[PDB]
Image (cartoon, rainbow, N blue to C red; front, side, top):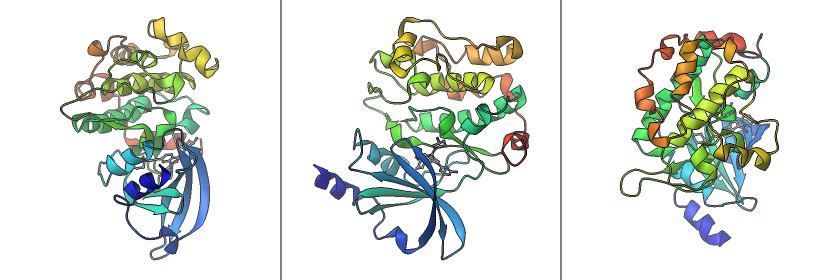
Amino acid sequence: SHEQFRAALQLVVDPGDPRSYLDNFIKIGEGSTGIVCIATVRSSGKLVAVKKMDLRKQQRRELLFNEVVIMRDYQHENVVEMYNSYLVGDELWVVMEFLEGGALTDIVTHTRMNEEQIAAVCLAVLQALSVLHAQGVIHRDIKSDSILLTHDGRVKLSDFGFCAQVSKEVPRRKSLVGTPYWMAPELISRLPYGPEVDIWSLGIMVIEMVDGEPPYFNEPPLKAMKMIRDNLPPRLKNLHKVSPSLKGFLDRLLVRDPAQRATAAELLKHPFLAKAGPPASIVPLMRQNR
Ligand SMILES: Nc1nccc(-n2cc(C(=O)N3CCC[C@@H](N)C3)c3ccc(C#CC4(O)CCCCC4)cc32)n1
């Protein structure tokens, strides 16, 4: 029931009304399960971002739990920091860090990134994924929209609306959740899957950074959704533009066998991630000056 769900939420969220100390709401997106705004904290003049998700308009209402239960003040240098969570009226509100460089989607649709910057983004994603897999969490929707930047080129991971916990005891999942063009091959076929789905999506995101779109991004969602199931790993339309180091690194990502996919903890020792430029390398890719 709606009311039982609201009651359960009120036991984990911070009480009261955040509209007391927030104003100048500026809308910035409609991402995953809710709209995302920016507000100023009048008590300080600082800026924060606010994810508003209405319980009434949800496919699965049970998705709202995880990001306030799993990502409850979990700190990490490469993961968007959540400050507070409130239940306002009929919507759940998440207040967090304001990442000012936009999403990575804006860069891959407008410019071409050199291997030195691809390695930077990947180093950050794997750094955060390593810890997230050790603690038992799967992102389950890693893609361009899930990656935010600061003004200084630092990269953080976001959009945990689809994440899940595995930990000990039961260690797998079988839920068909995410974005169609970015998911694993043992996804569309319901099979017990662990953190490795993320890694696969990461590989597809690598493809993004090389071409500006996931394999079969031109086909409608189901038209490609089924299309990847039988096929072998896709390959980039611009493979001639990528060095063999990137190609090897990516060849240990888009492995069809989940038991022969690489693990983020073991992917950090790879050679390609020596090409990782300082975060400043990413800075010229943002809209300040392309
Ligand atoms: N600059 C800035 N800063 C902070 C947030 C933010 N942001 C914009 C979103 C948005 O709508 N986008 C993304 C861009 C492309 C567009 N198509 C759609 C968006 C969606 C979800 C979350 C999330 C979350 C958490 O799970 C992360 C861990 C802690 C709990 C909350 C954040 C989002 N953007």
